[PDB]
Length: 339
Ligand SMILES: Nc1nc2[nH]cc(CN[C@H]3C=C[C@H](O)[C@@H]3O)c2c(=O)[nH]1
Image (cartoon, rainbow, N blue to C red):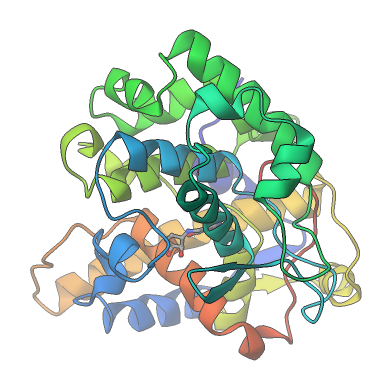
């Protein structure tokens, strides 16, 4: 049956018709990452320290915060950049995924317990629209899907887990793989699985980022100490492929680039879609191996364990900060609940 994400990705990358991993671009990105390796952008602390919307505390509240956001961590792109969902929070302005986090903090500050399953298990579509309200005329995408998943997720947390994601965390016994597995098996919307060449492959974008984010928000300590944190892969979404294609690590075929430039919508499980995700996932594994080797070849001792989580976080932010520079190669478009 099921290949795990890393195995899935290797298999996809090796049998890919429309997407290509370019060793030269793998080298480049590794070296761009090397010069940054001592800075907060490739430390676990950077998750809090570079993102003011992320929770400060390492408590049950923060953990449940990470849960609700990674539960809804899918599909923020809009049809045009002039015409998107924006949320204002404490006099600052956020679009995309950050507009979700703003929306959450905004609700918490209003006093609505949006990070509590007791609440979001029975929250209405009308309430959800309210909480996620935009400050432009344009709504966040798939709000109906965000409502349905909240209700399903809340119920399951209240029934199986005492209404707290901290309980799920503790049950994983400091294993990131077990936490990822528990999540995938307990919460339907996280089942980020499809087909390729007649084998079941897995990506687990949201499940993996949820584990990474649990790790980050608890600062790699306590219930968020994970002995096996380096086993987590990148989180295969639509932005990380874009920024790997920009930097020269990923190459797309004529036909694929055709779709991307015209804004033609991909479907979840389309081969080309699957190939982009799988190749991206494997691409990052290769950049990580390159970087570690470069760090070795300069006879160094890093001050923290570099892993595929941290590279992903970095490259995602890079995506965000350098959007204008990437116009030339668009991100692939899809509407699904998985990313
Ligand atoms: N691949 C990927 N997909 C994603 N969707 C949403 C996020 C949001 N994560 C944020 C927290 C730390 C990261 O630097 C990023 O600012 C994300 C990602 O960090 N990576």
